[PDB]
Length: 123
Image (cartoon, rainbow, N blue to C red):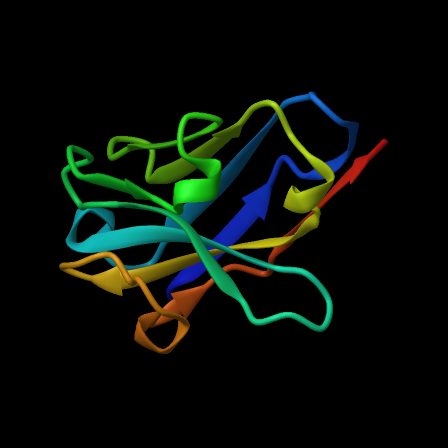
């Protein structure tokens, strides 16, 4: 009974900001590498950002690097994605994926998913 529950999405104007959260419960959180994926309707689900178990190692999709920040609080079992300078490009459903020991970099590698939270960026 491992469950990932997401929040913080919704609608915002271009240049705006959001903060996604993904609270985990069931397994031991620090043994999982957490990753944010996003999927626009009709396109393939793509990698956005990933963080290691300890929280030291972070990787970003080149596009969103600088604008997006991933982080995690291993005490409260949550991973965050702070989005800034949002473009219409970034409109999609954002999913949080967990994989044991090493963050997933491709969809197939993810062991546990969240329900997915919509982000829409109008202009």
